[PDB]
Image (cartoon, rainbow over all chains, first blue to last red; front, side, top):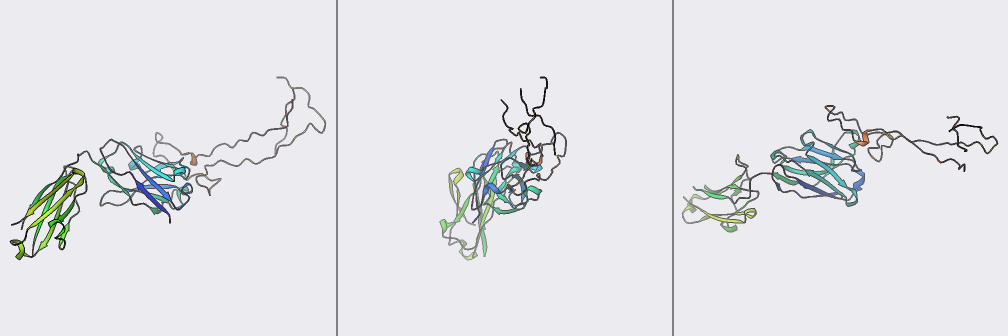
Length: 215
Length: 78
């Protein structure tokens, strides 16, 4: 089995540096040209860079040239990507990919990929969320707002309410803080008898908040 | 350095035969004798050819039999 394992993604302030790595097994690494390809959240794939079998020749997309440096150490079966003078727009899942054979001809396709490592380029500092109730089949929920970075987790009644729950994927705001919504559909009958608490967890800010939702 | 007589005999003549392989770029381990595909810089300022796209001069230095006033003189090429 050809395998490529990436490492080293995280958050980074604009202008600062970061270095991704990729470990290869199951082929002769030193006999393949290697690429990085990226994909901003919810957007399509963009090829970034290629390096020769030797490590001695690199080419770059216009979008990244002068701020990324692809490199390799064949003795460690390791591919690297060095991000410098970083921009908010450089935010994305970065994949290492084996060239399909056509390096020499300028004909790049990618026959093996890795998991991708997320690089998030933001100036905003770690922050726990404010949780507001979305009060009322009817429908109840929580608004988890102004937190950084990803992710939060959201349970209801500490794991007891599961059915009918929809935790929506986050959104980035003007502010550069994320805002999320979790809701549950519930029989209207039960809105007096039964309590609805959302458990909101933000490990990056070392936060757990329980919030009661009622009419 | 002044040049005098040519030694005669049958021990006065030597022949050198060889191949010089071309050095075109060898952009991968199957493309000996070829260069990397040409990429054109958008401007003069940004012109930055990688090694595997730059053919280079071939050169070979061949040792001849030792002579110690006597030097080997090259006379004919094929």
